Image (cartoon, rainbow, N blue to C red):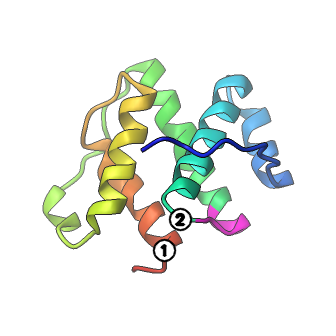
Amino acid sequence: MTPLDANVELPTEVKAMIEQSSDAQAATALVNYVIKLAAAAEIHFTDLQLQVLTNHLIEMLGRSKSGEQLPAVDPTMFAEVSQKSLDLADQVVQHIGHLEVAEKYVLSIHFEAAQDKI
């Protein structure tokens, strides 16, 4: 799905998280992308959710660059996550690049929580 066009103004705590990462440009771009993509899907994050999301997105971006292994995951545990959440997560993982497909599972829970579906 195409992310919405929008100016994104991140909360102080999210900007702090980003500033401390090893690439604020790419981390800012990624958080912005995810917010816009979710908004196109009619999903919105509270500022607390957005903090938790940002931390995870920074970790994923880091792994995309370092090559550090996918955190062990059992896909069967995600059988009842909505398809919409899984598909948005897959799009984000692919967009970042240099990640394993199964990064989508843990990321999908952020989208599921933002829809109040957990």
Q: Is residue 107 above or below residue 28?
A: below
Residue extending farthest to the right is 12
Q: Quadrant of residue 39?
A: bottom right
Q: Amino acid at mark 1?
A: Gln
Q: Amino acid at mark 2?
A: Glu
The answer for how far apart the CA atoms under marks 2 and 1 are is 9 Å
Q: Magenta part of the protein: which range?
A: 44-49
Q: Quadrant of the C terminus?
A: bottom left
Residue 85 in the image, given as x and y percentages of width and height = 36, 60
| Residue ID for mark 2 | 42
| Neighbour tally class for label 2: few under 14, some 14-19, many 20 plus, Cα within 10 Å | few
Q: Quadrant of the N terminus?
A: top left
Q: Is residue 93 above or below residue 117?
A: above
Q: Secondary structure at mark 1?
A: loop
Front residue of this view, candidates 47 and 5: 5
Residue 100 in the image, given as x and y percentages of width and height = 27, 32
Query: Is residue 111 one of those drawn in magenta?
Result: no
Residue extending farthest to the left is 76
Dots 2, 1 in contact, CB < 8 A: no
| Residue ID for mark 1 | 115
Of tags 2 and 1, which is closer to the observer? 2
In this picture, residue 118 sits left or right of residue 100: right
Q: Is residue 75 above or below residue 43?
A: above
Residue 114 in the image, given as x and y percentages of width and height = 53, 70
Taking the spot 17% from the left edge, 68% from the top edge, the residue there is: 79
Residue 17 in the image, given as x and y percentages of width and height = 73, 44
| Neighbour tally class for label 1: few under 14, some 14-19, many 20 plus, Cα within 10 Å | some
Q: Secondary structure at mark 2?
A: loop
Front residue of this view, candidates 18 and 72: 18
The number of numbered discs placed on residues in the rendered structure image is 2
